[PDB]
Image (cartoon, rainbow over all chains, first blue to last red; front, side, top):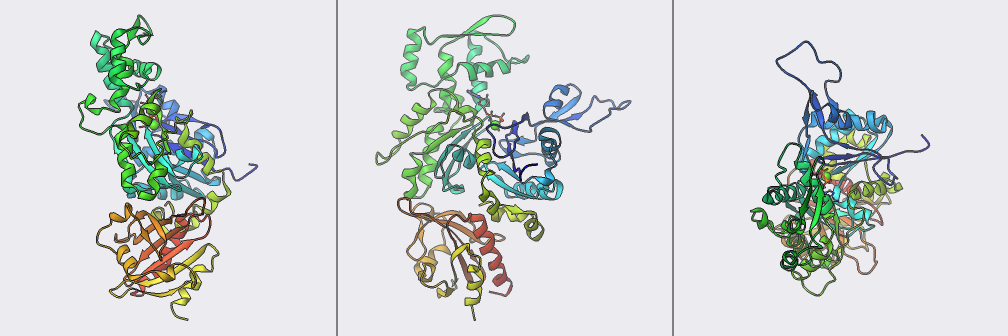
Length: 374
Length: 139
Ligand SMILES: Nc1ncnc2c1ncn2[C@@H]1O[C@H](COP(=O)(O)OP(=O)(O)OP(=O)(O)O)[C@@H](O)[C@H]1O
Ligand SMILES: [Ca+2]
């Protein structure tokens, strides 16, 4: 209405963050699911909307064949990944995509074809006037007002370390680790189930998770917190199930997050959060390294475990040369960092001397992403 | 007049501040460039590194373009379909930095350097579009 109104759409594997560029928070956060109606045998009819999406298809559940379109940041199905997008505009912000430019968010190491597909779609299908695809991690670093640094992104399915130089992700040094929320949840369950707390499943897996977000913290020294764990009681915390008992965790609080730094805890051969971060940096140019070590930003839910900063601050310091200042930056709002980042980016007059215009999509086609978007 | 035509064409924007056409085929030589800038000084050792054998070492040390320390960002110089490598200069203390994108062709290497605040995507598309023109004229 009273201005150009660019939009931001930060696509999480789980939660889709929509919004108008220039805001404080995603003015719409919905699950990324598409329910595809059913019942079987093959019936008397089914009715409206051959596909339901977002918060609505979420209730539906028992009637709809619910589907997750994105896996580990990467788009699994364009048919229903389109439905979520369609919905974002025509159902959430209730805008005609035709009049608003838009920032699309993406994952580090998004395959080429996915990029192009994403492009052809926004332009031919929704007819966006202009768009721009940005790596989720770059936007997070912007949210903390920086351009050069290293982001440690840990959401639900995987963790990436993205060393960014002046706003440009350096793919050669981007590292990916298969540990994130889920893993911490499955461990905690397995470790709570020890005093037969047996949550397992009856809608009981979400209880482990809520314990995880609510009661887990991170230890500065595992062994020593372990010893003090055994000496007991100002570290032993209780938790109330819905219908029932007040449970108790102790050793469990600081033990699940510790697998981050010690994946053998999870039976997996793998470097930890800290060494991974370190490995990326070594893969970078000798001249920017000192500026990566003093700009390790954290983003994503799995980074919210209290204490993760200091354990991070201490663990990298023992892996690296003294010559530099290790300085883990961990912004208070690191859950919505990515959207806020692009809100800021899509707020600048420069975003306009930065993106793909429809004219450009007509002259060049989807391959125009491998060009403009980096 | 000559390759100088393509150059003038490349700077006419007000966005770039340096261009250059360099032949890499066995006897490196700048064929035309913005004079009094940096690219004009690109040497055969330097050119011999961009069109190199390994596409890894420059990630650690870097590379100079006329004695300018540049950080490689993306590298697709040898990969078909793309033909591009993107760099960012390496300033010193607040000194502003600029993006550079070199795109290869059958015979030439088209370099392009943006002004202050020009996004790499701009400079890439532009340097790319030009490389395709030489690329179609057997150049
Ligand atoms: N406050 C918190 N403290 C600790 N862990 C948290 C907290 N909030 C969320 N988490 C956990 O960390 C992860 C958060 O990731 P996020 O919310 O970005 O996930 P998603 O959208 O479901 O998926 P993906 O990250 O794969 O895109 C989840 O596994 C969640 O359980
Ligand atoms: Ca997520």
